[PDB]
Amino acid sequence: EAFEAIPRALAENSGVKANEVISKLYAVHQEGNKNVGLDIEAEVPAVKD
Amino acid sequence: PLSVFGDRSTGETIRSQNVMAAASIANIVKSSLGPVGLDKMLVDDIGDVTITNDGATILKLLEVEHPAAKVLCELADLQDKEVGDGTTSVVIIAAELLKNADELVKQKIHPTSVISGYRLACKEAVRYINENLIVNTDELGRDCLINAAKTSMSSKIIGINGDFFANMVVDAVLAIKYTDIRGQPRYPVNSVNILKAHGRSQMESMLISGYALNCVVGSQGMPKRIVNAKIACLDFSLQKTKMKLGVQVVITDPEKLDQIRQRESDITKERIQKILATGANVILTTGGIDDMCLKYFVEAGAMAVRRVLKRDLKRIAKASGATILSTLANLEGEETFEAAMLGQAEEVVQERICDDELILIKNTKARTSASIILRGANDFMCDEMERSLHDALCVVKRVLESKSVVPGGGAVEAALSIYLENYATSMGSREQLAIAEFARSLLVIPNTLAVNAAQDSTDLVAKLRAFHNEAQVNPERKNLKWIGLDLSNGKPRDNKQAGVFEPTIVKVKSLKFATEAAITILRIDDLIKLHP
Amino acid sequence: FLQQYRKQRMEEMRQQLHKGEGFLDMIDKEQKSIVIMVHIYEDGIPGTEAMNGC
Amino acid sequence: RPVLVLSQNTKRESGRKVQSGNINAAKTIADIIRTCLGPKSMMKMLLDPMGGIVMTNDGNAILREIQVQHPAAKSMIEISRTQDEEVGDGTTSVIILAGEMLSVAEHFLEQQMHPTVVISAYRKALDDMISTLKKISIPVDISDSDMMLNIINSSITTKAISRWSSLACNIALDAVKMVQFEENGRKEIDIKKYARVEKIPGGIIEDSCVLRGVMINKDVTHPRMRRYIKNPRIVLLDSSLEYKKGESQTDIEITREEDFTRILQMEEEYIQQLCEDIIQLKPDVVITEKGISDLAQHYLMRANITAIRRVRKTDNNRIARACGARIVSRPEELREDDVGTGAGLLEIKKIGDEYFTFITDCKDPKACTILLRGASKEILSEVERNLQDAMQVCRNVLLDPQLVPGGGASEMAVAHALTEKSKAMTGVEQWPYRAVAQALEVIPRTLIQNCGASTIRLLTSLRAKHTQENCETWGVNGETGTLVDMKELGIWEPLAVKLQTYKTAVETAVLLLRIDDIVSGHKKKG
Ligand SMILES: Nc1ncnc2c1ncn2[C@@H]1O[C@H](COP(=O)(O)OP(=O)(O)O)[C@@H](O)[C@H]1O
Ligand SMILES: Nc1ncnc2c1ncn2[C@@H]1O[C@H](COP(=O)(O)OP(=O)(O)O)[C@@H](O)[C@H]1O
Ligand SMILES: [Mg+2]
Ligand SMILES: [Mg+2]
């Protein structure tokens, strides 16, 4: 769980909701995409490869 | 060359200093606006703690040195006195008006033109509010009062508790309703006695169908419950009779001393017997009662309460139909008491509230009164509940007196800003700029509301302005005037549909007071501070 | 025996039922009808704590 | 030239720092008394500023003796005082619960969740907590003395008086039962006024008992008066039995030889008349809240009457309740109904080196005194505090006859019920709801920590047990640190106490979560 502090900090500094970003990241990585992370070029919580 | 013993500030320096003071006062309370606002906890440097959200309380508790800031503090106090709600909004609006007016002045616009533009903008904003942004409460009913109370109690410690507190406040206000001459229904708030006591949760707050006294019986021998009460209200102490300054007792025949001393108390004994001979059961007095008359009342099996507050006694007498008697003297020169002076109530009980006892006068006849017992977790929460309840009662009184309400959530501010920006182009050349800046300054309320919710203030206010511009331009889409701010989700929402209402008098009085405060501060271009 | 202050014990047991410029300014203002008992002390020297608690 | 907006001494703090500081202060206040909960708690010595020593484990007393500067700590102290005043038990529990809820709230506040959402979730959780507590309650037959004694014992197993459990339970039950009163259709208990606790250092604790009457530290005014009366008729008074000045200025002017002697003789005659009026009722004991003159003492002894003077008003009211008398201020208005018949014995005996007055054989007395004998003053003070807790619990049970399982069983049951209910929320506020639900586990966790067993394994086992169907009464044994059933161990507590604790803790968390700005140092401006 301590690894969640990195995407959470990135989302907080970017200005979005960290919980939504983390939930989306878990969903995508459960789907099987290991190269998906936070997209800071968006006004809403979003992820991209 | 002046040789004045003091300091002098002139020009842009003093104007900037005044604007700084006003902005600082605004920033003190700007974080406690709207439902997403949060309270402040003040310490009185002696250990006293005050947790509150009310702007007037915060500004009164603080000690302020700059006089331009004292102007805003007393402006908030005036808004609290004359309306009871919108105390932070008026301060914020006045500070924003002063800031934008100072910007205009620094742009070499003469202050007289700015003041004239502000006056014109305030007049036209009031006219537009009265003519376009009012909803009659006749076609809404009790739901309008409930929604107004809920909106008032948002941003307060009784927010989610609103579903219950709104019903309690509405019932309390409707209980004390009376009509004066000209058939005008006047609702006399501050007649609802608010009693606080820590203990059970807020859900356990009780609304008394009668009156509640913060006092107990004077003697433990008296009964603590009387069913068919006959209240006798008195305004004189029941003690041993003592002669006044102009009367002096001098004894030359020693045989009269015993008679004198006996009569000294027999006078009061006869008065008590005369009072009790009419069937009185509850005796309330503003003065004190000594042990002798307490024993008299004990033997008769009747209530007797001393040191009752004058306002409480007046309310009890008015509700129960009793008459205050400062003395026992008819127009025949005698000393008599008749049953026509007795008030009646369906029950009088000394109840226990968290290890302490208070007297409940239940179901007074010939008039209905009300009182509220607030139960909390500690003293501070009870005080904050009392303040919020007073705000809600004032809001309900305003709504019931004047039957016009306005949409909440900054809808009125956005509509006014759009209308005034459109309107400024039809008046003058520099008062045009003043009216435009007035319109821009009116946008501070929705901006603060959005900021306090950690929402995108710029986008939300832009969408609100677009909705109101479409409403004002298109005459077939006038239903968008009610679109306000839904801070729970950060989206525009029809607040009239959502039930977010405020009295129109709140907006009107806040605008007028803020305009006068800004004009008063803006007239200063020089300050002389004499050394004490 | 009045010299022993028989009421001293009852008064004690009911007492526990709890239920530079400043020196000038706090006395220059406020009502003259109330009694102010100023206390003078210095840390370290014994005897101040007892009367402070009193 | 110090031009300023606010005063020089005004200090303002706002933001995340204020919330963190408030939550940390509440946590540390909880940590102060965390170890004083459960049957295996430890004593704490408090050095009173006035030189006294307070040795106790009651949460309210320990928190009251502590002076703090942080306003959140003051709020927590006020919370403890409110809990003590409302129900008389659960102060440590409510403090610990408030601290735990504020901790789990800080956890969310570190993220980007607004405090209003947390407060709304807390209020919904509190409503569900109340519902579940009312659901899992059981009724009690108050007429069963054994059940009441067991309830009081379960209340006092965590105090120093637990060594003498049956004696303390019987004392508390008898005091509460005999102080019960009903007049004019109004029912009352009034532990505060009547049921006085009188402590006399010395002797042994097993000698403590509740008397069928009152007992005061008073002696006869004159030694010739009887110190032992079989069936006294007691008369109570407030007015002095001595010649006092009138209310008005009443200067005399003596110009004859015999006026001075006549005035003194009439003083004596007035005293004689008052004494004759008192004697006309033929009483045996006269009690006055004010002084009795020596001539009055002589005139009363002439009629074989014992007189006691300078009695406190509360003591006189207690005597009136105990012996069925009515306090009278004017002897000339003394009625037969005012004479107190019902006291079965009045006796003045010396305990140690001080005379005490006993009225201790009243039939059907509505007031009583609890005579405590102990090792010293501090031990007797702690015993009195424990007896107050027991009497408050007994009164709560009598007024509200529902019971709730103890030993943390109720906490775990309510936590499991709220956790199960939270599964259907499907919202953003479900997380604070579940967090504040699970925060109730701090009570069994604290019980296990104080007992000394392994916290994690025991909590896991208790949660697994509570996931079953009929396991709401399964809690933690406070002595052996094992999972037992409170329908077997017998630890049950009033529903009112648990309800008050839960409500107060949740509302304290709500109140402290609302603050985000602090300004201090300003003048009182009274
Ligand atoms: N439920 C709500 N939704 C949106 N806005 C609201 C709601 N309730 C109140 N408001 C707005 O929040 C603003 C702040 O009001 P408040 O600060 O509580 O009054 P005061 O200024 O007297 O303290 C008001 O102007 C009102 O329009
Ligand atoms: N015999 C026992 N076994 C296990 N737990 C007990 C026992 N007796 C009491 N408890 C628990 O101890 C708690 C009471 O602690 P206590 O010291 O009374 O705190 P407070 O004074 O705040 O009520 C209750 O929650 C109860 O569940
Ligand atoms: Mg308001
Ligand atoms: Mg306890």
Image (tube, rainbow, N blue to C red):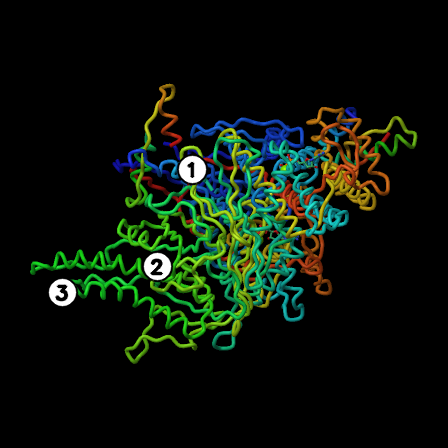
What residue sits 30% from the left and 34% below the top? C24
Is D349 or B511 nearer to us in this picture? D349
Q: Dot 3: what SS? A: loop
Observer-side mark, 3 or 1, equals: 1
Q: How many marks?
A: 3
Q: Secondary structure at mark 2?
A: helix
The answer to whether the residue labelled 1 contacts the one labelled 2, judged by CB atoms less than 8 Å apart, is no
Q: Are marks 3 and 1 in contact (CB under 8 Å)?
A: no
Labels 1 and 2 positioned on one and the same chain: yes
Identify the amino acid type marked 3.
Asp
* Chain at tag 2: D
Q: Is disc 3 in the same subunit as disc 1?
A: no
What's the amino acid at mark 1?
Lys
Front residue of D338 and D390:
D338
Task: Report the front residue among A44 and D16.
Answer: D16
According to the picture, the residue beneath numbered tag 2 turns out to be D279
Q: Residue visible at 56% across and 48% down?
A: B198
Residue beneath label 1, please? D350
Tell me the chain of label 1. D
Give residue B253's mark.
3
* Badge 3 residue CB within 8 Å of ligand 4: no
Asked if residue B405 lies left or right of residue D217, the reply is right
Q: Residues within 10 Å of mark 1 (few under 14, many from 20)?
A: few
- Asked if B184 appears above or below B399 in the picture, the reply is below
